[PDB]
Image: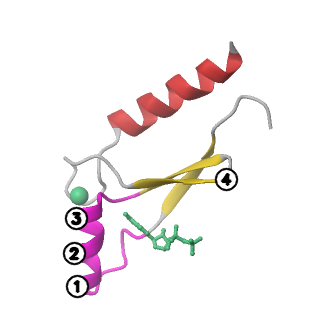
Amino acid sequence: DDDDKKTNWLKRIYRVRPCVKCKVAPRDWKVKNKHLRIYNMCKTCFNNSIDIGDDTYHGHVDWLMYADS
Ligand SMILES: Nc1ncnc2c1ncn2[C@@H]1O[C@H](COP(=O)(O)OP(=O)(O)O)[C@@H](O)[C@H]1O
Ligand SMILES: [Zn+2]
C-alpha cells in the first residue's frame, strides 16, 4: 500500500532529525489540511527563541500525508 510508504517515511523523518536548536527533543508539528507541518524546533526552544529575540531557527517543512497528490 503506497499510503503506508508515505506514512513510514514521515515517521522516520520525524524520528531521526530532532529540534534544530537543542538537538535532543523531537520537533513541534501540526496537521494543516492534508499536510503534516514539521516545525524546526521543539516547543520549549521555539518559545525560548521568542524571549531571546532570535528568529534564526524559525521555520517548518510541510509534507503531503498521502501517496497520491
Ligand atoms: N516550533 C517551531 N519552531 C520553529 N518555527 C516555528 C515553530 N512554530 C511556529 N514557527 C514559525 O512561526 C510562524 C507561524 O507558523 P504557523 O502558525 O504554522 O503559520 P500560519 O498558521 O500563519 O500559516 C512560521 O514562521 C513558523 O515557521
Ligand atoms: Zn529544542
- Counting residues from the start of the chain, the first of labels 1 and 4 encountered is 4
* Circles 1 and 2 in contact, beta carbons < 8 Å: yes
- Counting residues from the start of the chain, the first of labels 1 and 3 encountered is 3
The residue labelled by disc 2 is 48
The residue labelled by disc 1 is 51
Residue 15 place in picture, x, y as percent: 35, 34
Using the rendered view, name the quadrant where residue 64 is placed. Answer: top right
Q: Secondary structure at mark 3?
A: helix
Please identify the quadrant where the C terminus is shown. top right
Q: Secondary structure at mark 4?
A: loop
- Using the image, tell me which numbered label, if any, was put on residue 61: none
Is residue 55 highlighted in magenta? yes
Ligand 2 has an atom within 8 Å of the beta carbon of the residue at disc 3: yes
- Using the image, tell me which numbered label, if any, was put on residue 44: 3
Q: Identity of the amino acid at label 2?
A: Asn
Residue 23 place in picture, x, y as percent: 22, 50
Is residue 59 highlighted in magenta? no
Question: Which label sits in the foreground, 3 or 4?
Answer: 4
* Circles 2 and 3 in contact, beta carbons < 8 Å: yes
The residue at the far right in this view is 69
- What segment carries the magenta color? 40-58
In the displayed structure image, the side of residue 17 where residue 31 appears, left or right: right
Residue 39 place in picture, x, y as percent: 43, 58
